[PDB]
Length: 54
Length: 54
Image 1 (cartoon, helix red, strand yellow):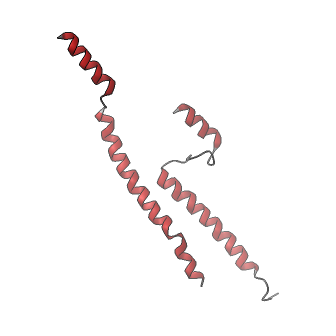
Image 2 (cartoon, one colour; image 1 turned 90 degrees about the vertical axis):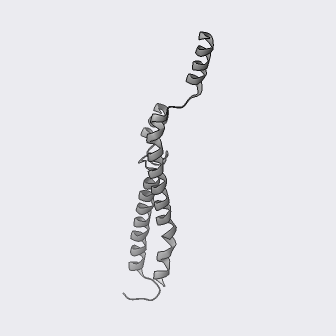
């Protein structure tokens, strides 16, 4: 019984993710994608100023 | 001088406009990457140190 517990705990240490760091990465990447969408929206308008020349 | 065959003022205006466009491009690129040193083009030495260190 104790050996089974040790093997299962070893599997858990081998694969399981640490959710505490995941909680910070989630919010950071949400802000990151929002900033990326904003920057791509700004970049899309580069050709709009050309019509003013004519 | 007021010939129709050339227009230097438009030439300097275009030079300044392209310079400002390049500055805005690099700024929006650092906005959507979140990194002053995005690639080896930005600055090779610290970028190399960052790659090895990470």
